Length: 55
Length: 55
Image 1: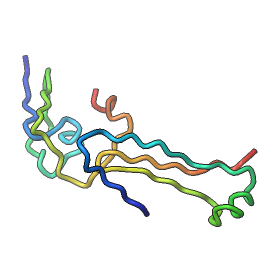
Image 2 (image 1 turned 45 degrees about the horizontal axis):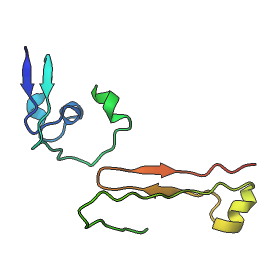
Image 3 (image 1 turned 60 degrees about the horizontal axis):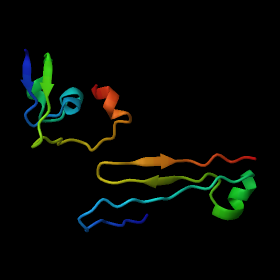
């Protein structure tokens, strides 16, 4: 498969473009792996129905 | 503007609400402002409501 370590970035954050997920720009995959040690460092935010925007 | 932290080691459950008046005057009467507003949040949460005046 095509595996992509989210590393510290969470898919959503990798999406929006957290100051630190720049690394994951224009990325692609088959199976995005979200990590625990993961965090977001950028203007706090709330995504209503985050679940879906994710899924 | 009130804040009430959670220090204990367990999930706290808050049950609150918002009041909807019958007349644009029942508001005035009770809450002065012509249009209520309520917000309850946390570092990860956030939800805001505005009263629907009516009958």
